[PDB]
Each structure stands twice: as structure tokens, then as C-alpha cells.
Image (cartoon, rainbow, N blue to C red):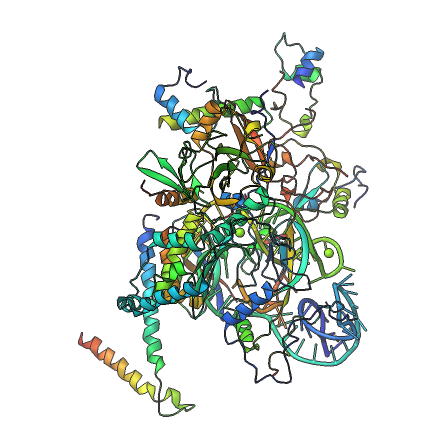
Amino acid sequence: HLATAEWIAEPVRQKIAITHKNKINRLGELILTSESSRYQFRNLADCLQKIRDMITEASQKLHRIRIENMNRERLRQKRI
Amino acid sequence: PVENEAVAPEFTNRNPRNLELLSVARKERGWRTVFPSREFWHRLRVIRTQHHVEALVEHQNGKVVVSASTREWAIKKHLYSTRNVVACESIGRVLAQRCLEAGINFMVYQPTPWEAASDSMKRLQSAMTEGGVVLREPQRIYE
Amino acid sequence: RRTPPLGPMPNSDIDLSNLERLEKYRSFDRYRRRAEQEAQAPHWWRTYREYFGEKTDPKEKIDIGLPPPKVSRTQQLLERKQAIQELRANVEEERAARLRTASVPLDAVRAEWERTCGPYHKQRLAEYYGLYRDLFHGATFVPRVPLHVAYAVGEDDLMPVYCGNEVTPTEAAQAPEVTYEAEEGSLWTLLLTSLDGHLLEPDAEYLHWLLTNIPGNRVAEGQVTCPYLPPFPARGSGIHRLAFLLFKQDQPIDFSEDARPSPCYQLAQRTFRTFDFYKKHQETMTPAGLSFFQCRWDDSVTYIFHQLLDMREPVFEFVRPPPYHPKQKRFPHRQPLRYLDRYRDSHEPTYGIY
Amino acid sequence: LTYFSARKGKRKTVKAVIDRFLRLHCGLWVRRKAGYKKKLWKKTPARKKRLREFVFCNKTQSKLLDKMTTSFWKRRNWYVDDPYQKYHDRTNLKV
Amino acid sequence: CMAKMPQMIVNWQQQQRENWEKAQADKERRARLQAEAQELLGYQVDPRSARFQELLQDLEKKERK
Amino acid sequence: RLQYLIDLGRVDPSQPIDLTQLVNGRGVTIQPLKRDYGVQLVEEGADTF
Amino acid sequence: YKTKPTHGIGKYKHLIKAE
Amino acid sequence: WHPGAHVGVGKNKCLYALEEGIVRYTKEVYVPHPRNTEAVDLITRLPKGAVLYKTFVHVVPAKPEGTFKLVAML
Amino acid sequence: SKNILVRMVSEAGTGFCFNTKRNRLREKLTLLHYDPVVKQRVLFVEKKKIRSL
RNA sequence: ACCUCGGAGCAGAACCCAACCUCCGAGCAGUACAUGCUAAGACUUCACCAGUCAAAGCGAACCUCAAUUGAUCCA
Ligand SMILES: [Mg+2]
Ligand SMILES: [Mg+2]
């Protein structure tokens, strides 16, 4: 669970929450998997390293997406 | 155990346009020897007759998606000639509007050399670009 | 060996005794036009279309719907000729055309288009997107009655709704405003359905917004059987096309198989089959209006999954097949050393007994 | 080739195959394609990369090279920083 | 060397361009040979007078400078 | 394999494990004339150890 | 192909002038 | 022969499959590219009303691009 | 003795070099090329000859 | 007189096919300098050697001809 982790700060917690909505569970608990290697020790290692990278970067096709978003938001210009 | 929670492993969507919207569909690559390149998903075909001007946005299957015509009363009543640069650029603007209407954000138009050098087709392209459509098809995803 | 031709092979009609008198393809454009003529036409030999085309049945598609009104073609051409007459008689249009400085009202053009011949093109778009083959298993109709819908974003601005538009779940979270220009008196029925929203089976659809017995254009008075709930396009599932359907209820009909309680968030309740639904309830009425749009996953979809629907949210993903590789062989010849990596399972090494 | 020597009465390896090729304990052999350092100016990029890439040897000349060299060169070896530990063994081979 | 590359790259463009202008300068002179007739050996006869005239004029200008 | 050894009980963990003890338990044979400078530890078997 | 009825479908030399 | 329907062409005029599936041969019309001068001038010299044909290869895509599968029910 | 095969060099100092054909009469020439090390189009100058062709 | 390679007939229609058989040629040339790197899958001059086509990705823009040629060692 993210919000219960006291060892993380308020802004970093909310940053991770808003940035990684996809992984958060219904009950609010974050999950993350790794299955690159056969060694579960190394899997857990890269898991927690992903965690640390997320923490650091939080403490710090897309073209097409933007295109159709601009098209939609220029079309939707209408009055009641 | 909830009937709403019940979910199958595989999800079957019967929307043919889903893949081409996700950029994942397969385009009919080939025909490098023949002039019309089939590696598209939505092609624009323009017909410049000596009486009227037609435009059709269609799918690779050869079937029409949307149409614009100078023969139509709704369009020709606000005009002077059915073939001038004015008519060409107006049909271009209307077709860009109709594409934004039917959700068509991307499409393709391969002209001949003289058709490309013609000022009418150039102003049509500019009209569609300012309408909000680009005449470049995205690059397919796979690997 | 030779075999005679089955059907008339091409270029057989022309004569060869007289060749210089013949007219030629002076233009690649004319030759191309003739090429597409012969491609349009059928052929007895094997062709590209009979392999890669939808193979529509030869029978016409059944549609017992609103016929066109009896418009006097005589007076129609009369008034059109008069219109073009004063058009050509005008004075400024000459300079406008010869200087390329004219324009046209897009909104008005759209208005008279959807008034005159819009319905045919909207039917074309429907049969393209696949509404008919999935909803009615082939049968069609013509949406003679126009139809406008809007999702008011707050209250200042609004997202319009027309055939084949993107709609955000955040904007579709509420009920839309609707207009279909029918105060005649005869009743109407409206239903918002999701075609590919069902997940447990194909040939299934959900229903989000049902209204029946709508006297005139006013919509608030129209009773509701299936209350409102926005769509829930799952992340990675792709895109889901949502259809507005509108039928001309000639006389009030009851709803028992159809009567559903308070929303209760039950997909087994929201699901049904439009085919037998129309076959049962709609034998008195016919289609009058049709529209649709396209929707995708969103944070509001996640919210309604976790809170509203009272269930976990699904998470799908597109997956390509595995890359083909032929059988191995004990002694490859002239194959690079990465042939073994093409088949190795683990990227990391392993030692058998050590 | 030299099936019995005069000093020990044993088979003898030709150092040519050793300098040219490499045997993996799977039984396979590899070689550098001929002409990868000659006349590169006229050769097209695809051709020269095909020549640079390593390749295996079919079973006849594999068995030939085996008969030519001795068992000391067929034994298992555990080198350090030798990238071919992944290839000295075989994986998922049927028939 | 990288920090220096852009200047020499612009200089390379200028080299190409000046070679291109020299190409125009000589091909425009080659364009008009003679109009009186279509001879075989005369081709390289009449123009040499004007060519040597221009060369001597340039040389005299250089000496004057 | 090391777990297998210590379970079979031929090598005693009570004392310091050394290469000579491995060779006397026959955990690994060695060929010094074949210029093997020693023994490597392998990642395999990190689990259940 | 020759044996099949589609033989001679592509030929054009007799359509164009010969020289 | 000529390509078509997911079949490319190498510099040596060899045909190669771009997708995985079944092959078919058909006969269709041949509209050249304007840069092909000899083809264009042949089309011009051609008499009106007459049209040529040429063979084409077409691989029928057997399998789809992929499938949507459930990853996590959360 | 019409043409000549000549080597050109990376002026960056990387030491990356390659070869190409040149006309015997045309003078020195300096061409852009993609240095795999520097990883962008950069000018290489040709120094000497190797063999005629 | 020839000794290598390529095109055409003999070999007419998937492949291959010889003769001190019948004909024509080649032992280069021209343009770029991404004529950069990597990679699935396949062809293959009847073995091997060699010789071929190429999806995709990175990194970039926005090759033609028909043969047009040469292994290892060694320098
Ligand atoms: Mg072979
Ligand atoms: Mg590529």
C-alpha cells in the first residue's frame, strides 16, 4: 500500500499515484512484477530497483495521440 | 464469485476499424510495380471532370467511406463554376470537415505529377491541412 | 496443348484490319479510367476481388422503413434552374471566381446536406463501420430523420455527437442532450447501445440509455426502462463504437423481458440481442434515426470500475503470435552462429551437472 | 592422417584445422567465411557482412575435421570471458 | 574537432557552390559556338579568337590592378 | 550440488570448507595439468539453499 | 499459361504498330 | 510475373512474401507509374477501348495480426 | 589508368577511414559521410591513393 | 583452335541437360557517399567453395547495367 508507506514523502507518494494509475489496485495497493530471469532473487532485485527509479524520477504514437486530441478539441468548439 | 466479475481470457472485438485506429492493422503492402500504392488504410480519390468535381474517401477494400461532390445541390448553390480553383478548394474544405466529422484524422492521397503541380490540388491540400487533416499515413507498429 | 477460351477474352471486340483509323488513349488518365472500368466489371477468370472482397450476397438488403416523399421532380428542377439562373446572373461571383477569393457557409451546407441526402451517406457509413451486419445480421434502413446529440462539458461548451466521432468517458459520464425535430405527435423510442462492450461472448451488446413513449421532441417526459450508466472501455481493449438508435413508435407499447429495476449494475441485465429485440418489440415501428461515436479507456472508466460497477477493472493487451522458426537440425550448413540463439529459451546460461 | 607416430604411436592433429576452425562440444564447427578481408571496395555491404558473419559446417566435413583432429580438441573446456559457453551446449533439439 | 566542424562544413557548401557557378560560367560560354553553318573542323576555329580575346583582356586587367 | 553434498553428509559444514575437502568429498574432480586454476561458483541453485 | 484458356490475354504487340 | 497483396520485389526482380499465408495467382490490369517512360508511351500508342492484362501473385493472409488477451483483473 | 581507388579519413581524429573511386584527372575532393563513432554526417578528406582501376 | 563468366536456339510448356554444335557479348562504365550497423525467413548454377533476395529495428532522408571477375598462405 502506497499511502501507508511512511518512509515515502507526501509529494512523492501522490506523484507516483497520479503517474502510475495503471498498476494501482482497487484496494489502493500498488503491485509490480518481474519475470526476466529464472532467478527470483534477481527478479525481486529488479523489482525494487524499478521502485527506486520511480521514486527518484518522481522526486525530480504520442504524435498521433496529440493529433487526434487537437482534432477533437477543435471540433468540439460549440455553444449551447 | 460475481457474475459481473466474470470475464473471459480472450476478448473478441468485431470492429474492423479498431486495428487501423491502433496502427496495428496490416496494410496491403506490395504493388511496387503498379502505380496506385495499396499500403494505406484510407485513400482519397479525386475526379476532375469537364462538368463537375468528385472526391471519395474509401478503404483499401475498394468500398467508399465518405463522399463529396459538386453535383450536389447543397454544395453547388453557393458557387459560380463547378470546376474552378474556388470549387476545388471549397470541396477540399468540405471534405476535411466531413473527415473530422466521421472521425477520419488520417488518410492518403497519391497524385500524378501534373495533378500535384496543379494549383487547384495544392490549394485543396492546404485547405485540408488547415481543416485539420494531414496527408501522411502513420508507420505501422509491429516490432 | 491448347484449350478454347471459356468466356470472351479481352481485346477481342476490336478489329485489326483497320488500325490507323482507330482513336488511341491520348492520355494516361483515360487509360486509367478504362482500367478501373474493366476492374469494376466482373470476369470469368480468377481475379483479385473474388479472393479479397466483402462477399455481399446478391440479394438486396431488406429494409421496411420510411420511404422518400413524393417530390415533384418537375418543380424541383424548375426551382433549381431558377436558382442557378440568378446565380449566374449575379455580378460579383465573376470576380470572386476569377480571383479565387470566395468561400461557402460550412454550417448551412451541412444543414441542407443532411436535410436532402445526408441519410444515404450515413447509411453508407453505418454499413461500413459494421452496424447492420452485427445488429440486424445484414438488414438495413435509411435514417430519414436527422438527429443531434451533445454532451455539455460543464455548461459553457459541449462535445457534439455525430457518426464516427471520438467521445471521452469523462464527457459521457452524464446524460446527453438530444434533438430529432419531431413534434408531430407520434411517439418515439431511443436507445444507446454498445456493440463490442460485452466481454463474455460475441454477438452480444449492452444498453446504457433507454427511453420510450416520447411524445414529440421533448425528451424529459420520455419514460426510462434502463437507467443511465456511461460506457466502460477497458484499457488496452482498444476502441468501442457506441450507437444511438431511434425508432418511430406509432402507438404506445408496454415493456414487461425489457422492464429492468434500478440500475443495480448487472451486465446480465444490461445485455440482450438487438436482433430478437427488434423482431419482438419493433414490429409496429421502424427505424427513423441513427448515429454513433467511438470511445476508449480513461481514468473515469477506472473510477467507475472500482467504485460504481462494484468490481475489479480488467486489463487487456494486444499480443502478436510467436515468430515462426523451422525445425532445428543437428548440423546446420552456412547459417550464422546466432542460429542457436534463435532457439535458446533462457537468455542466461545454465550448467547441467556442476 | 598420420594414424601412428614413430615416437609415441598415437594419432596427430593438423594445426591447420585448429587455426582455421573451432569445435563446440555439441559436435559442431564454425568458420570465418572466405574473402572477408579482400576486395571489399567492389563488394556490396550485404555481401561483405555475409562474409564477415560466422557460419557452421555441414556434417560430412564436420566428421572429417573430427577425424583429422584429436580428442583433446573435443573435450569440454571452461574458459573465462569466453562468449561461447552459451553455444558449447545444445538446447531443445529433436530428431 | 567537432566544435570546429560546422565552420568547415559551411566552407564545404561554399566550395560546392563556387564550383557550381564556375560550371555555369564555362557551360554558358560553351553554349553559343557559331551560327553561320554546321561545319566539322571549323567548330574549334572561330571561337578561339573570342576566347583568346577574353583571356588577354582578363590578363591586362590583372596587370593593371 | 553443494546442497546435495551437505545433505549427503560427505562434506561437513561444521568445519571450514576448502578445495581439498571438496576434492576429498569428490564434489569436483580437477585436472591441474590441464591448467584449471580453480573452481567457480555458479548462479544455479541460489534457491533452496 | 498455354494449355489454359487464359493464354494470350496479355499480348499487346498485335495491338500496337509493328516496326 | 508481378507482385501484389503482401508480396515485395527485390532488385533482382524476385518476388517475396511479406505476410504468412496461402498464395494465389490471378490476372489483373497493369497501370504503370508515370516515370516508366516506355510503359507510358505504350499506353499512349495503345488504341482506345482496348486494355492489357498481366499476371499477379497474392498471398492470402492466413492468421490475424494478434489477439487481445486478459493480463490482470484488478 | 582512368580511375583510382583512394582512402579518406575522419578529421575528428577518430581514425575512422574508408575508400572510394575517383577520376584520375579530377582534383582532391572532400565528402560527407556517417561516422559510426561520432554518429552523424561529418566531412572526410581523401589523403592518398592505393591502386589504379 | 580452345581452357573463366554471361545472353539466345538446340532444351517449343516447372527445373536440369552435352558436342572441336549454331550466334552475340564481358575482363567495364556512370551517379551517391547512411554504397551505415544490425536482423526474421528463404533461393542457390545439381557437392563444398562460393553467389543471391529481404521483412523488421537503430540510426538516417522527406543505386542503373547482363557478364563486367580470383581461394589460402604470404607481403
Ligand atoms: Mg546447391
Ligand atoms: Mg527496412
Q: Position of residue D42 (x, y in %)?
A: 55, 61
Image-quarter location of ligand 1? bottom right
Of B68 and E42, nearer the camera is B68
As drawn, which residue projects farthest toward the top?
Answer: F14
As drawn, which residue projects farthest toward the left?
Answer: E64
Q: Which quarter of the picture shows residue D68? A: top right
Q: Which quarter of the picture shows residue D85? A: top right
Number of marks drawn: 0
Q: Position of residue E2 (x, y in %)?
A: 35, 48
Q: Position of residue C5 (x, y in %)?
A: 73, 70
Of C146 and H11, nearer the camera is C146
Q: Tell me if residue B32 comes above or below residue D55 in the rendering.
A: below
Q: With D38 as the anchor, is A49 left or right in this view?
A: left
Q: Tell me if residue C267 comes above or below residue B81 in the rendering.
A: above
Of C229 and A66, nearer the camera is C229
The quarter of the image holding the N terminus of chain H is: bottom right
Residue H30 in view, yes or no: no
* Residue located at (59% from left, 59% from top): H10
Q: With E52 as the anchor, is C133 left or right in this view?
A: right
Q: Position of residue D60 (x, y in %)?
A: 77, 47
Residue D42 in view, yes or no: yes
* Residue located at (32% from left, 34% from top): C155
Q: Which quarter of the picture shows residue G1? A: bottom right
